[PDB]
């Protein structure tokens, strides 16, 4: 008997602390989650934090696919750590690449990973949300994603019908596969998340993990017809949601540092406003790393960028 929409506003605006737990090992990618971070975030005025987690490398590959305890223990440190500063939290299964290239083979392990996770946290504050799986793609096609997400729901609810669940989209989590999304009729406490990076060439200009991203380096943002496109996409989102009775959460959105601060502030500000206009919850892609809004070793936010994220 929970209202997801009421839960979506609880979540509100927040941010990702990535390049952390979704890396092969925490640190591998530069960021190690400090307990103090939750202070900055809170005092900073954020309602929640999203913590991407790569469980797939911290769990046995043979039945019953048990999750290794030191890691599990580490996630606990991070959960209550955010809960302290009164921040709400979103955890998920992030970068499970073998599942994206061979779903059927890893489907079993996946369902098992959630059974464990849901149980481990089934009685935690209701301000903790469960994100099924980050940006399904590859061979984990849209129609196949629908089947897998439903079974994760059955795995979760059987353990708990208290926490709101976040369901993404396929084809890398953007709007391309939105239409094709199907959340079971019986699920009544879920939120739909979309990653919005749309001006991809702009947001990912120079992303070393994206092939051919070199041809984007140097792009700028802040033009007319420019926003009309994005606006029609936000409307598409909005129309889907109104016709599907599901709240929206923009789980990720941000511009890579190689873009010029100016067009990064214009895009963020714009998209944030368009997101609040439609009353969407959302989280800026990552706190301090290569997409950062807070420079770790130098203690200082990019206040303008931050000003754009905060109301
Ligand atoms: O690859 C660019 C971005 O794609 C998103 O779908 C992932 O969630 C981010 O972690 C990643 O940085």
Image (cartoon, rainbow, N blue to C red):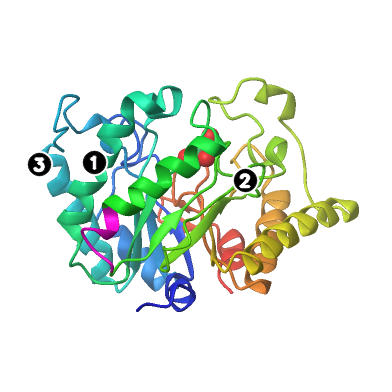
**Residue 271 part of the magenta-drawn span:** no
Per the rendered image, the range of residues in magenta is 156-161
Indicate left or right for 112 with 87 as reference: left
Q: What residue does disc 2 label?
A: 180
Which is more N-terminal, label 3 or label 2?
Answer: 3
Q: Is mark 1 within 8 Å of ligand 1?
A: no
- Viewer-nearest of labels 2 and 1? 2
Task: Determine which of the numbered discs, if any, sits on residue 2 in the image.
Answer: none
Q: CA distance from mark 3 to mark 1?
A: 13 Å
Which is more N-terminal, label 1 or label 3?
Answer: 3
In the rendered image, residue 225, in percent from the top left (x then y), is placed at 90, 52
Location of residue 117 with respect to 65 vertically, above or below: below
Task: Determine which of the numbered discs, if any, sits on residue 113 in the image.
Answer: 1
Q: What residue does disc 3 label?
A: 69
Q: Residue sitting at 27 percent across and 38 percent down?
A: 55
* Identity of the residue furthest to the front in this view: 185
């Amino acid at each position: 008997g929970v209202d997801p929409f009421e839960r979506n506003k609880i979540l509100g605006r927040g941010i990702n602390i990535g390049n952390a737990l979704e890396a092969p090992n925490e640190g591998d990618w530069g960021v190690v989650i400090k307990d103090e971070f939750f202070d900055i975030i809170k005092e900073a005025g954020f309602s929640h934090v999203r913590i991407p987690i790569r469980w797939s490398t911290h769990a046995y590959a043979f039945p019953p696919y048990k999750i290794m305890d030191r890691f599990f223990k580490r996630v606990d440190e991070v959960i209550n750590g955010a809960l302290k500063r009164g921040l709400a939290v979103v955890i998920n299964i992030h970068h499970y690449e073998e599942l994206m290239n061979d779903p059927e083979e890893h489907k079993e392990r996946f369902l098992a990973l959630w059974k464990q996770i849901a149980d481990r946290y089934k009685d935690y504050p209701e301000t903790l949300f469960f994100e099924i799986l980050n940006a399904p793609h590859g061979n984990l096609t849209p129609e196949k994603w629908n089947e897998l997400l439903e079974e994760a729901l059955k795995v979760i609810r059987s353990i708990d019908k208290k926490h709101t669940i976040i369901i993404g989209t396929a084809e890398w989590g953007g709007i391309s596969a939105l239409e094709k999304l199907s959340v079971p009729k019986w699920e009544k406490n879920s939120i739909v998340t979309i990653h919005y990076y749309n001006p991809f060439e702009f947001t990912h200009q120079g992303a070393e993990w994206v092939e051919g991203s070199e041809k984007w380096l140097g792009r700028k943002w802040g033009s007319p017809d420019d926003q009309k496109h994005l606006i029609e996409e936000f409307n598409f989102i909005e129309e889907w949601s109104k016709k599907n009775k599901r709240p929206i959460y923009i789980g990720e959105f941000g511009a890579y540092r190689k873009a010029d601060l100016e067009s990064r502030i214009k895009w963020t500000s714009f998209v944030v406003r368009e997101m609040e206009k439609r009353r969407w919850s959302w989280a800026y892609w990552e706190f301090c790393s290569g997409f950062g809004v807070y420079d770790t070793l130098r203690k200082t936010w990019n206040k303008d960028l931050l000003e754009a994220l905060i109301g």
